[PDB]
Every structure is written in structure tokens, then in C-alpha cells.
Image: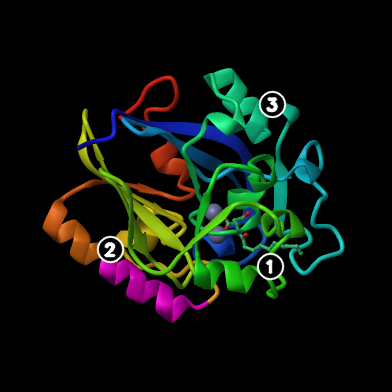
Amino acid sequence: MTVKKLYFIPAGRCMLDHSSVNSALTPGKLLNLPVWCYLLETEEGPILVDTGMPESAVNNEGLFNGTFVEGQILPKMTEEDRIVNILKRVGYEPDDLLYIISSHLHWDHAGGNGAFTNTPIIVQRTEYEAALHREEYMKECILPHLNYKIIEGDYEVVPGVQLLYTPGHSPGHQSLFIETEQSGSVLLTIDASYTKENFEDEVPFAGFDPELALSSIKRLKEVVKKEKPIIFFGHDIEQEKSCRVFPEYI
Ligand SMILES: CCCCCCCCCC(=O)N[C@@H](CCO)C(=O)O
Ligand SMILES: [Zn+2]
Ligand SMILES: [Zn+2]
């Protein structure tokens, strides 16, 4: 009925201009933000939520030089942060995983997807379709021959693991509502809100369709009012200071 353990796994970092976490701010200060993956230990097996950054980001802060985000996004990734290495240190190989869940196919969430060539990768149809043509998607995040499990809308992965369709930040973004043995209800917003203030205070942040993103935040607030979960945001430096991280779990 519940997930046995929910692990927060640091998967490197990325510098992002602060105007991407609060659209009102003047550009020109970068923030060193966490990149997360999550590992769910379930009765049916281990499930990995997101896959970190692509190998091209390893020791390559200048990855986005020459692109429309030059100077605004700089990966902070070492060899240790490649998802296969993270998993091996934790105690898994890619073919051990039951599912991969892609919140969305942005570069720091699906950069590791190519490592999983057998495991089904659960991703929203609207996200998959966007990734095929929109400029903000890297080739590494939309590789053609992976075992995609394309879904549409809300979806129950296994008992205790619910996906909530939360488009706006990206065209097919999805968040997770998890029931854990130790903590009960947990909401992982992922990038439906980078920070607590994006969520609680509806502070605008980077997104494909900010209006739609706000509607998804409103939807999540309805879920929160009903379920009273503990809530974790996508790239929140303040919250990171108090997060239990691997080998601790919730
Ligand atoms: C030109 C190749 C792709 C350029 C990537 C554009 C960035 C799109 C927005 C994005 O992926 N933001 C990241 C946060 C900062 O790394 C995210 O959604 O987590
Ligand atoms: Zn994103
Ligand atoms: Zn993100």
C-alpha cells in the first residue's frame, strides 16, 4: 500500500540566473541550485524519478555557450554525478529499475535517460511531443529508441505512487504524490514550482506557459488542502538546507 522508502539523491548542481526563479528580479546574479533525482523503494521494485544531467555537462560549465541561454545556465557536474555512477554507489545497475519516471524532459531531468535502454520510461505524451521540436530540448533527452511508456494525464504507477499532470513549466510536466511508510503523504512538485515562494506566493518563474503553470499550482493547492502532504520543491536552495538526503529517507 505505501512506498517503503523515498530517497532524495543529489545529482549535481547548476548555476541559473536568479531571474529564472523570480521573473521580477534583475538578471545578473547566478544561483548554484541543486539538481535532484528521487529513488522510491516499493514492494514491486525500485523506481527512479529523473536522471540528472547529460555526459556532455561533465566538467563543462560552458555547455550552453553559443546558445540562447549562454551565461544564464552553467552545469556544475563531475563524473560522480552521472546517473549510472550515482546508482552504482547506491547499489543498483540500470536494468535493476522497475520504472523510470520523467517529470519532464528538460536537460537536467532527462539528461541520463539514454542509460536506461530496457526499463520503461514513463513520460507525458505532451512532453514527448514537445521534446521532438522545441529548442529548449537537448538531443540526449529525447533519444528515439528507448522503451517509452507514454501516458496522458494523471496516472498510478504502483500503489503509493501517483503522477499528477502539472503542465505549464513545460508542455507535459508532471509532479508526484507519494504515500510513504514513514511519512504518509508527500508532494514532489518538481518544476511545477522551483521554490517555496513560486508555490505559496505564486512568484513567477521560468516556464513554457506561465499562465498554465499558475493553473497547475492552483490544482496542486487543491490537492494540498485535501491531503495535507509535506511538500518539496524542484530547485530550492533554502529547503535543501533541511532536506533529509540519501542515505536518510522519508
Ligand atoms: C540549446 C540547448 C537546450 C537549452 C536548455 C534551455 C533551458 C530550458 C529550461 C530548463 O531546462 N531549465 C532547467 C533549470 C536550469 O537548468 C530545469 O527545468 O530544471
Ligand atoms: Zn524544467
Ligand atoms: Zn528543473
Is the residue marked by circle 3 packed among few (<14), some (14-19), or many (20+) residues within 10 Å? few
How far apart marks 2 and 1 lie (CA) works out to: 25 Å
Residue 189: which quarter of the image?
A: bottom left
CB under 8 Å between discs 3 and 2: no
Give the residue type that dot 1 points to.
Glu
Q: Which residue is mark 2?
A: 220
Is the residue marked by circle 2 packed among few (<14), some (14-19), or many (20+) residues within 10 Å? many
Ligand 1 within 8 Å of the CB at mark 1: yes
- Earlier along the polypeptide chain: callout 3 or callout 1? 3
Note whether 126 is above or below 138 in the view shown.
Answer: below
Q: Is residue 214 magenta?
A: yes
Residue 207 vs residue 41: left or right? Answer: right
- Would you say residue 30 is visible in this rendering? no
Give the residue type that dot 2 points to.
Leu
The tag on residue 136 is 1
Residue 179 vs residue 116: left or right? Answer: left
Residue 38, how many percent across, how many down? 45, 38
- Earlier along the polypeptide chain: callout 3 or callout 2? 3
How far apart marks 3 and 2 lie (CA) works out to: 34 Å
Residue 69: which quarter of the image?
A: bottom right
- Earlier along the polypeptide chain: callout 2 or callout 1? 1
Residue 187 vs residue 118: left or right? Answer: left
Magenta highlight range: 209-219
Secondary element type, mark 3? helix
Q: Quadrant of ligand 3?
A: bottom right
How far apart marks 3 and 1 lie (CA) works out to: 25 Å
Q: Choose between 143 and 15: the one closer to the eye.
A: 143
The tag on residue 80 is 3
Q: Choose between 69 and 162: the one closer to the eye.
A: 162
Q: Main secondary structure of the magenta part?
A: helix
